[PDB]
Length: 252
Length: 251
Image (cartoon, rainbow over all chains, first blue to last red; front, side, top):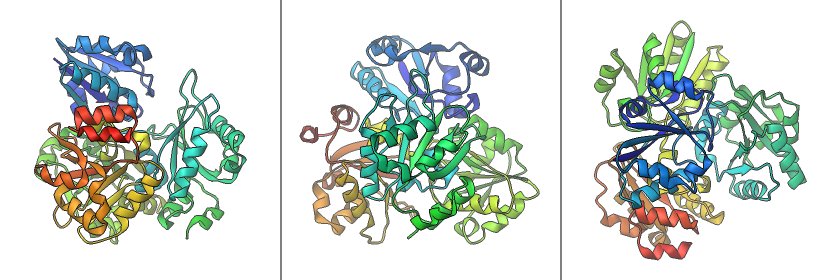
């Protein structure tokens, strides 16, 4: 009896850890969810890589009907594959909670997550990131409030974009932020497309200027910069994200 | 030719991605550093898993003398292994910048990071974490100021503890914070030992009370809680971190 949460990493089947791959091969039953995020890989591709069957679970199986998955783990060794690192999405912590409360032992096999990837692709300092927010298809005052609060303590803001029913692009998120608060248009930001693919599109400029960029296909994430930049951060954005020269005004 | 940064993940040799392992096998030269963090495995145990020699680099090789590693990568396929993810420290982005300026192609194979593993072990919401800080063995007002700035926006604080010359434990970190600002003693915090080991020691209590816990050997990390908690965070801290009932006052 066991429920193991296994991170898939960011892009394809080889992003799983060796420990994770071993856990999936050892598992009695293997499930996957593509609600909290998604990978390039399809379920057949995963099946050929693992050499065993993989069953896709939907949103209801992770929320209201989470008891079903947990019931399977009362008599078998079950694996739930999640894009990225398990528990970055709050959903998983609730599943784990329910499971432990029902006496089912859990285990988490960690994966690489998008925040991390954004730091290596941009050169922004991970310790400088403040709270994150999700820009939803439905208007909200939340992303703007989080950005302002983070700027108040000189911290960056990682923005995740809506995935459902269709993935939102950086262009739509810029529009959304500016509609909510006109002052967002001149804040410097970085758009990142397909983080983890190795063929990312990364561009830093004033927010409104990111609508001019062809970010390619989703998934997309954005970063709104802090009030200031460390000189190393400035140098890295200039080299990795094609930032304009006037970004140096953020360096104190 | 190629300079690939590869995260090792959190605890042992199998924490590396399958892509990371293939990159190490395809590389001409493989280097590792235990300066930014470290895993349980020794250099010899990595060499056994990769089936090839792995050369350990020191701080000077990663900082002022990084041009040496970059020169190797101009004619060979080079891998630099780093505990956790390679760019969660700030050390490594400087190497990447220097390499790209010299026209050397770089690639990053991401790994699991502590910065995200604490959420799975505690039930704290990742989106509520604010800026992180490192508690150094020497006195500094930095960690306390970061904690305070994060609580001003109602955010959690991840605290990394000094690794040199030896790794700092939660007990010493508590002493340090309370010496810097006595009010730190009553703030709720979570001590986490050996995150990623699967055998972690996790405990949530007022800061001063964490000195009562036997967290065992390093490495240790801590979280200082935000001003309030979501009800689900409280529920998870009570089930996973043996939090005291009085923590519900933060809900």
